[PDB]
Image 1 (tube, rainbow, N blue to C red):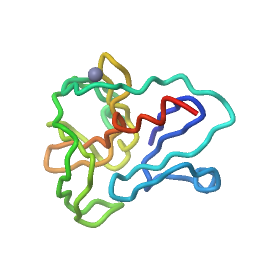
Image 2: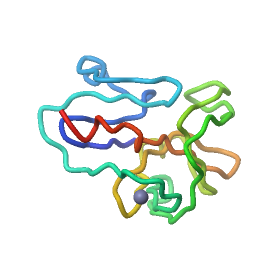
Image 3: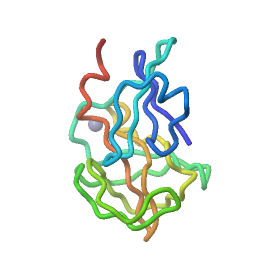
Image 4: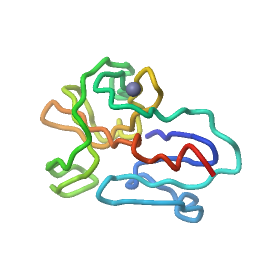
Length: 140
Ligand SMILES: [Zn+2]
C-alpha cells in the first residue's frame, strides 16, 4: 500500500483505490494503474520533474529502501499478478529488484522528488508507475 500526497491530490494505485477515492475522483487510467482523488488537507510531497533513471524505492515486504537504476517510462508487457491479468501497462519503468503485491504504492524518489509508485513485480523485476509527466499535480 501507499500514496503520494501533493497539493490537494492523493495518488494511489488504481487497483487499491477506495470508495472515498472514487467518490472524490480527479483522474484515473487503468492502463497506467493510477488514480488521483482530491483531498481536504494539503499534502507535502514534491513530484519530480526530470528524466532521472536512478533513485531509491521503498519495499515494504523487506522493510528496506533500495537504490536502483530504472528504465524510461514505456509500454511494458506485464505477466499476470494477483490484481491484473497479463497485459500491456503504459508509463511503466522497470528496475531489478524485489516487488510483491503488498509493495504496491511504495515511493520511488530521486533528487527532484517522487518519481512514481510501485505497481508491478515478479521475474526479479519491480515496475513503477511514473507520475513525472502529470504536470497538473503541481497546480490547481
Ligand atoms: Zn530526478
